[PDB]
Image (cartoon, rainbow over all chains, first blue to last red; front, top):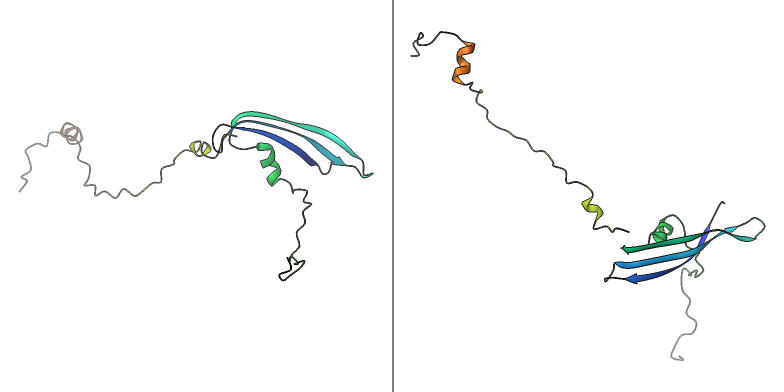
Amino acid sequence: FDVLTFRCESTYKFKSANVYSSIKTTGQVLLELPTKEVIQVGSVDYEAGTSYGNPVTDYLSRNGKTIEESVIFENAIPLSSGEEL
Amino acid sequence: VNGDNVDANYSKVMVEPRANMKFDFPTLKSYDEIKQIAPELEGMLDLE
């Protein structure tokens, strides 16, 4: 595999204000073939108790870019102006 | 997982060194040691 997209979901439970009592992080990992077929390579199965952060997301926070769909313009354009609104 | 408050307690506090300027008069030997270095010379020279 050359590139992998991790489409992931998490379930946190808390024990104090910013510590976690349990983390369950599952998800699917994905490969784009040159024939544009998407086949799953493997899975994520993380589960821990009494943690302070999610390792799975912190690994993806630094070692990859997010698949960004909300692409923001450089200068936002106003649609209508005046008192009309 | 274990938090950034814990892993600071994994590194050890090293000691920076300073200088220890003393004055150090020459180290006086003990008197029973001073007579093994010099034998029966006692009471012979006038110290004045």
